[PDB]
Image (spheres, coloured by chain):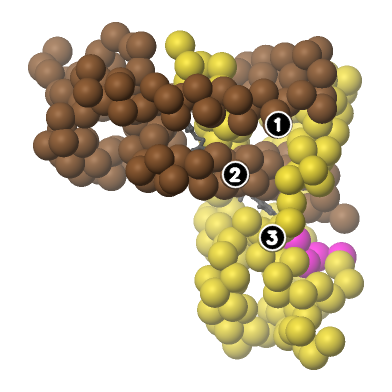
Chain colours: A brown, B yellow
Amino acid sequence: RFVDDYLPALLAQASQLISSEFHEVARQHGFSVSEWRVMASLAGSEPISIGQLAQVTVTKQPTVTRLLDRMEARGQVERLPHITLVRITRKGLKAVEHLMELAREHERRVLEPFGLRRAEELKQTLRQMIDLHVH
Amino acid sequence: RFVDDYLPALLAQASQLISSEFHEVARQHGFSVSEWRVMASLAGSEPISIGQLAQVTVTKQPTVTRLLDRMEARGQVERLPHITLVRITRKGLKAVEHLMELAREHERRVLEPFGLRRAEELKQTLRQMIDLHVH
Ligand SMILES: O=C(O)COc1ccc(Cl)cc1Cl
Ligand SMILES: O=C(O)COc1ccc(Cl)cc1Cl
């Protein structure tokens, strides 16, 4: 059966199942999916361009720009001129840091049955595939 | 940097990049993303329930039901009573079979740099993760 062993279907299914688990936690802490992705990807980061943020959050750039409008109004991010750069503020970092700890715990739980070797292999393969296909 | 080594972000990014590549081909052959997922997941399948189809196509069930309304009007799928089951028709199979060959070729190209061992390891890990987290 094709779908059972077709890589893009496996990636899409695994991604949605794991993400859906953590999105429940994120919402219980006041975060939408997009807010979580933006703050977690900016935490501990130099300012990056709106285009880089859209890439790493897997979000269309027009959508990211409207999201940053409201996140900047809430004091959680700041846009700055170099192209437009964006950074997390201290308020945003304090808003997200506990949730990031919870995300690490959940990821640990997802990966523990597989063992350190298989978990690192998976992450390295995914990183290599991303770097080969990103524009 | 958190996002660089956080499994759900890696899965979401790799999934979107690989899928976006094949979706260009699919549209050039007349298929939307959802139409492609439905027909490719039903090809060579016993009839399955709408809920199973929603799961394997990573699509919300209300959306799948409206999609099947129009795909059934086009003669490409058929809904049948057991719960509602759904199957691909011969017309649908003939519509999608070439695109499935192209999808296999694209997947081969994505996986070839990694070698057979790493490619099979990735697919087995993804399958195991899906089976551990699906409801
Ligand atoms: O939403 C999810 O569960 C996975 O996607 C992400 C999660 C965290 C970050 Cl920082 C970036 C992305 Cl794309
Ligand atoms: O759309 C994509 O590129 C990947 O998602 C799929 C692809 C094919 C099938 Cl059959 C099922 C799914 Cl979820």
In the image, residue A96 lies at what x, y percent? 36, 27
At 28% across and 17% down in the image, what residue appears?
A48
From the viewer's perspective, is residue B44 above or below residue B109? below
Q: Nearer the viewer, residue B59 or A43?
A: A43
In-image side of B90 versus B20 (left or right): right
At 63% across and 40% down in the image, what residue appears?
A18
Q: What secondary structure characterizes most of the magenta part? A: helix
Q: Which mark is residue B55?
A: 3
Mark 2 or mark 1, which is nearer the start of the sequence?
2
Name the residue type under label 3.
Gln
Residue B14 visible:
no
Name the residue type under label 1.
Val
In the image, residue B116 lies at what x, y percent? 87, 23
Q: Are marks 3 and 1 in contact (CB under 8 Å)?
A: no
Q: What residue does disc 1 label? A: A110
Q: Nearer the viewer, residue B79 or B22?
A: B79
Q: What element does badge 2 sit on?
A: helix
From the viewer's perspective, is residue A107 above or below residue A131? below
At 50% across and 41% down in the image, what residue appears?
A25
Q: Nearer the viewer, residue A121 or B43?
A: A121
From the viewer's perspective, is residue B58 above or below residue A117? below
Q: CA distance from mark 1 to mark 2?
A: 10 Å
Decide if ligand 1 comes within 8 Å of the CB at mark 2: no
**Part of the protein shown in magenta:** B39-44
At 81% across and 13% down in the image, what residue appears?
A117
Q: Are marks 2 and 3 in contact (CB under 8 Å)?
A: no
Residue B43 falls within the magenta-colored stretch: yes
Q: Are marks 1 and 2 in contact (CB under 8 Å)?
A: yes
In-image side of B10 versus A67 (left or right): right
Name the residue type under label 2.
Glu
Q: What residue does disc 2 label? A: A21
Q: Residues within 10 Å of mark 1 (few under 14, many from 20)?
A: some
